[PDB]
Image (tube, helix red, strand yellow):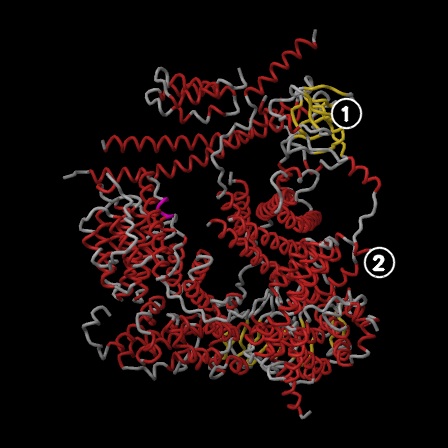
Amino acid sequence: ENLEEEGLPKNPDLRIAQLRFLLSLPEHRGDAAVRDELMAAVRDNNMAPYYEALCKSLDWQIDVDLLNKMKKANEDELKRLDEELEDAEKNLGESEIRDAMMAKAEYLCRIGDKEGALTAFRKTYDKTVALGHRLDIVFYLLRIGLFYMDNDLITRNTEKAKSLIEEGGDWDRRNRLKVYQGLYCVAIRDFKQAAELFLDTVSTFTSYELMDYKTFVTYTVYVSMIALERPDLREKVIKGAEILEVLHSLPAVRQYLFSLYECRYSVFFQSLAVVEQEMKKDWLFAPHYRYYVREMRIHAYSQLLESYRSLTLGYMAEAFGVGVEFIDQELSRFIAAGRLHCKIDKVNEIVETNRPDSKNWQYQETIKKGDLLLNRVQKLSRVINM
Amino acid sequence: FDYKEQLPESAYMHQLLGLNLLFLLSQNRVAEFHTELERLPAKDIQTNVYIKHPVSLEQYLMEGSYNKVFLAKGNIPAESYTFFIDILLDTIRDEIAGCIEKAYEKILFTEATRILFFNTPKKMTDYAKKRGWVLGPNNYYSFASQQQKPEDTTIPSTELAKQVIEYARQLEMIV
Amino acid sequence: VRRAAVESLGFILFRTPEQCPSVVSLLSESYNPHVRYGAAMALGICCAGTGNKEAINLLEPMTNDPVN
Amino acid sequence: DDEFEEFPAEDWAGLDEDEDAHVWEDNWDDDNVEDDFSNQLRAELEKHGY
Amino acid sequence: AAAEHSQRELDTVTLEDIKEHVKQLEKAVSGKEPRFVLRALRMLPSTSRRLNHYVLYKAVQGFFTSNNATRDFLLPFLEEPMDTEADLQFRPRTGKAASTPLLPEVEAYLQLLVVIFMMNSKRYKEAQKISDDLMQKISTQNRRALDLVAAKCYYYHARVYEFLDKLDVVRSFLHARLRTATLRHDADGQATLLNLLLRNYLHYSLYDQAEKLVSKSVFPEQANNNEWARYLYYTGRIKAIQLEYSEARRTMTNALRKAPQHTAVGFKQTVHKLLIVVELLLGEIPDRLQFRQPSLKRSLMPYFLLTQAVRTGNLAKFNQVLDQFGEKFQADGTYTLIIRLRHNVIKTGVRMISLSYSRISLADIAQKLQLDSPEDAEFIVAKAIRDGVIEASINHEKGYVQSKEMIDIYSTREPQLAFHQRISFCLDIHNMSVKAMRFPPKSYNKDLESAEERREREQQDLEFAKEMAE
Amino acid sequence: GSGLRQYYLSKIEELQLIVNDKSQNLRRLQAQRNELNAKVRLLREELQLLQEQGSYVGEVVRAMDKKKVLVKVHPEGKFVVDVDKNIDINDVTPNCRVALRNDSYTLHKILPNKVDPLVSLMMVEKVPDSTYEMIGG
Amino acid sequence: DLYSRYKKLQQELEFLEVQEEYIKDEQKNLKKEFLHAQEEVKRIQSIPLVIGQFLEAVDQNTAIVGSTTGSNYYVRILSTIDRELLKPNASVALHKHSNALV
Amino acid sequence: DKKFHGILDQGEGVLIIFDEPPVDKTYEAALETIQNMSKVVDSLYNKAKKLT
Amino acid sequence: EQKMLLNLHKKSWMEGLTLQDYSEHCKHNESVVKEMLELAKNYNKAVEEEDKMTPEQLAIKNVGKQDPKRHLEEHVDVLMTSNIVQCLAAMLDTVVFKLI
């Protein structure tokens, strides 16, 4: 019952970022409920810089009275925190000084003053003695980075948190860092690492400031079905006790997972459409909702073609509950991309599977990645010469 | 193009320029064809018929629309364009058969009549013996010639040894 | 043979004394003590009587050479 | 430096609001113009009378 | 008068900067190394904006210190200030310096400054007059470092005519100066003049003339990067128009590499457009990341749509893109190369059809490529097979195309060839980097044993031998 | 009124460009050769240098007048040693580690300072480090 | 004086060519002599060698070592000694006379 | 479930078992080495741009 | 006598054309590449550490700790030599010992 109380402080509230993303979407710009919730959060937290950014980016009408009241509250609270810091530096000790700066930085982060929050957090970190307090400041920076999707901040603070966790053997902070890293890997389309971290922290999840446990398990399943092989998916997700216990309360996600695992391809396609509409509204999966779904489709196709030498187009269409023309177009597109190891005899409408050696698939990636690294080397030498 | 500031726009200029472009196409000097085409303004290339016809013919020739190439004779912009057309056509047939040998493994005798754009069936026989096509008893021309593969049967050991020796040079000869 | 080869440069370049403190200057710091002696002797032979300041500047550190 | 003011610098007129600002292995297939898979599946579910 | 005070405060520091540059040129002459000229021209674009009428007047009337025909030439072409309160006489030349005539290096530099201000003042005819006088001045002289300045003059000498929109009277002068620089082994001037001649030829679509010029002339290897970029761009454009797509793509990639890393945005946009068009013409695919750049996004959006249409391999989509952005492509000077992309669209579509379908009906091929009739698709597929685009065969009686079974790529020599190209490039990179390592001329053999400390050992060891043995 | 003066100037400048290029290349080659030769010479002198006797390691008790230092050689008790002209007497602090020559025992280098006695004592005591964050209640 | 300058420049160019050829030859032979010096410096490692304990690395080429005779010495390190093996508490072989880390 | 390597031909009702080759550890190690050396090149990029 | 002594360690003509066992050659290649994997992983850290490291520690801090750059160079040299020699020898043998 004390689950949410275990999590780290909810600054910045990632729900605010999710609602801002929802308002950025053309479909849900005019949603009165989303706007009401975001305005309620802004008013409760007195987020004057965030209110300015909201009205500037979204082209809203700034309530002058509300803005003035929130700005006055921010100024008075900042004055109070400055007075507390001034009292601490003269009378109280270093611990109270650090506490006063932590309060100031937390208030700056809470009101959306991103740059001021970063400056105050750096100052607080500079004279913070306790290792765990420093790591908490690093987690604050990580949450701020996730709030604005600041890749540089997230990467730097992830490296710093890894070093701090290595110094002091804090496995709880290690699990929290794994959750944060999995969230970032979801944000940057690194579904393999995201799935690995999520499965590692599926039984130790306490980061309720990022997401609800049900949402975390849904994300874990979503990344696992795209990043895991069939035996790994069976051992970790299908037979996972915690995941199954959570899925008992999520019939849609359980249907989506088991339809793929049990080869109910029409049910899987319907659940994939539902999942796609879910990803489109999630600020973490929005850039990849087109990618992820496509990959899932490929997986399904690949699975249906993995065990069979050849399959008629009509059989594929019946299995997926779609038309023969749709199967033809999808299979042709995915074979042309080199993702499906089969060829279509449209004269007889028979998909014949191939077994290309792993050597070719390794050689093509070797060429691609070596060319990328070679371009980096060339451009670096170009920078060096002049 | 040079004295066009003082000279007025000649009515026959575009027709003669298209004639030049079509002639360049007839002699397979396509590289010169594009350079001379670039001299024209970009508007009359897609607008003026005298320029539109040769560039479209070049597109059809490059993409392989040989039937459209043959049809281009009927809708020539001017009578003067006629002569060069024939010069192109003699190539097209010899090009079309070049595809037939490498694409079709076996084609019927009459089936090529529309493919080779031959009017008289007699005109097939002389062109075939010029091409050296082995006619089959079933009126099928057997084009079995892909057996002359890239010849992967032989390892270019000399070239590979030269390349590896060059690697050794670039690793050691530097000093 | 190396020492005599460096020595012989003076008899060839004495007509242009300014050239010897350039061709031989690097030889005067070589690992081989015999080549260093030949360099000094080439400076002496080529720039004899001329009082070349460059050759004397080359010879001055050579008077503190580890080899006798 | 000898900057290339000779060439006509076409105006930026771009979006400085972090249009993409992402680092992935981005490929061309994500840019294929098409409706969402939900719309395609919905439009083909009723194509069979279902 | 705050604006006047601030304007004067920048005018004096700009005058000091021009003084520093003229001192750099004079010391380049004094030290006989022309490379000191470059740092004078290194700041030239920055100073070109940091000058006005007052700056030019002060510089030209305190800088010559001799009222020759030059001061009778450029003083009347610029405005003069009033009796300003701060009459700071800016006379860097005093005594014999004032009496002595200015070096040919620096009079040309000040005349370039005047020409640049005339261009920024849109006085194109007056700029042409001043540049003609300047060209007489630098054609009469035969100095060595002046060539480093001279090239820059030429770049502006043509530039003023670029706004006169003639570019034809300049061709004879450019050819003559190119010859006089080539005969003099003037690398910088020859490179600049070659780039200017190529630009002049391409301004009038004289691609044959530019192709001949690049065929016979030899570009200086030790040329500026900013000139190498222009030369590579122009040669790539020539190759693209002349259907030499591979070398065109290589040259455009090299030009993009040698472009300035922070500035020259318009040059980047033009080269990116042409490189995308050439890469589509070559049958490859443009890199997606280049369309993500903030500066290039708006410019390449039509080219992004064109690349999408070509990648889809659909005739209808490509024709829609053409009918939508034909005017934009024509304004960008790439429409002629865009027209040729129809064959590449058909080729890409045939390639994916062969890669996806083991046996596919010809009518289905025509439908997928949005062609007119399957009869035309027969000829198209036959041409693709003959050219080696796709390994397949056509069954005319049956009416379909059977794609050949894919051969094991890794069991052939193609991976060896690709690895060969990459390995040779890597070894070339290593050799180039090693050859670029410079050791400063330190006093070698001083880290060895010192004479006094080495003598210390000889004396102590003499005592060792004299005492231990006894 | 010049004859082949222009011809002479052209020939002279044509030779001057090549002369400058070859001079720069020769300077680069000479730098490479000087580096390698210095390496060779240092290698040959290292064989003689390595036969020079090693220096004792001592602990400084206190500096004294006339540039003397009271040291304790590691196994060999105490000595009153001179100070090399390259070592400042004000840098010879008590309990410092110094290098003394083989025969003269002359202080010729100040070695990096040893472990602080307090640090050494607390290493064996080894109390667990702590902060307020790990104290509960 | 034009001809004198031109001829002097020609002689200078030919002399520079000679100098560059000689420098390349000297580099070619200096590599061999470097290898020979590397080979001949190994006589400092000739047995018998005392055994010490590597205590500290003062700088690149000198170190404090504790010999098994019981005395700590500040000696030199042979340049051809793999410094990646100079871990703390590592047994080293020292020259019997000069105690140098060989 | 990847318990064995093969395919099922329904038309003839025959199971075809394949003697698959093991994946090349050399190519996997080369790919990860390329990735790590790209990271090295990024570090060199930071060092170069910061110090020049 | 100098020519006679030059025959010391002079390898026989047979082993000049002798090809190394391809199983062991592949195993060695895989092992060395797997080593360079960890070597590059450490090389990145070495670059970052030497970015922020004082000039007195350029060599002192390298004492007792392996240098990823040096081991990487050694592995590269070894693999280049081995693979180039094997390829060249195989290509020579494909011409010399031929059935036709």
Label 2 packing within 10 angstroms: few (<14), some (14-19), many (20+): few
Residue flagged by tag 1: what amino acid is it? His
Q: From mark 2 to mark 1, how far is it between C-alphas?
A: 48 Å
Residue B56 lies in quadrant: bottom left
Residue F59 in percent (x, y) is at 73, 27
Q: Residue at x 44, y 22 (%)?
A: C58
- How many numbered marks are there? 2
Q: Is residue E116 above or below residue A327?
A: above
Label 1, secondary structure: give it: loop
Looking at the rendered structure, whether the residues under marks 2 and 1 are on a common chain is answered as yes
Is E37 covered by the magenta stretch? yes
The x, y position of residue G17, in whole percent, is 38, 33
Magenta segment's dominant SS is: helix
Q: Identify the mark nearer the N-term, 2 or 1.
A: 1
| Res. F136 mark | 2
Chain letter for mark 2, please. F
Q: Which residue is mark 1?
A: F74
State which quarter of the image contains the N terminus of chain E.
bottom left
Q: Residue furthest bottom?
A: D49
Which quadrant holds the C terminus of chain E?
Answer: top right
In screen coordinates, is G97 left or right of E352? right
Residue E126 inside the magenta-drawn segment: no
- Find the magenta span and give its range: E35-39
Residue projecting furthest to the top: E470
Q: Position of residue G3 (x, y in %)?
A: 24, 32
Pick whichever, A26 or B80, lies toward us: A26
